[PDB]
Amino acid sequence: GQRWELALGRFWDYLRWVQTLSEQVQEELLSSQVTQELRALMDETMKELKAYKSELEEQLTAEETRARLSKELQAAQARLGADMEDVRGRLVQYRGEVQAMLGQSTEELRVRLASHLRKLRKRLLRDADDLQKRLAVY
Image (cartoon, rainbow, N blue to C red; front, side, top):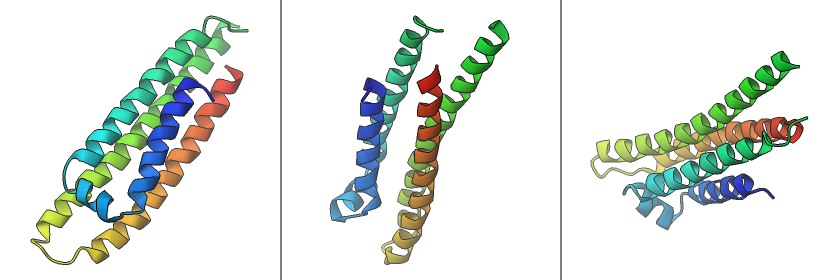
């Protein structure tokens, strides 16, 4: 229950809501509200993540190994940020495709988005787990 975990949890809960593609989700998806609110949550998560790592380095248990673990951690951090950006990007894409439909039914478009989001979210949880496991030793 660390700070950065609570932040990610809020990003994750918000994303779970979006996955439902409910009436309200849809409303905010055609505006920039969902992607904007997701960016704020992502920024907060990365911000707390950096602060946490910084504080962790204050009580660390050779050099080559330390430099390797710090780089491996840095990579996991990047994967997660990238993951969150990929989700945002996919949602931005959705918004554009609906506009391209010129008013046509978006049922099928939503079916595809739903399936893709599920996979992007799988990857995000997978990387978050990896990142947490790496911080656990660090």
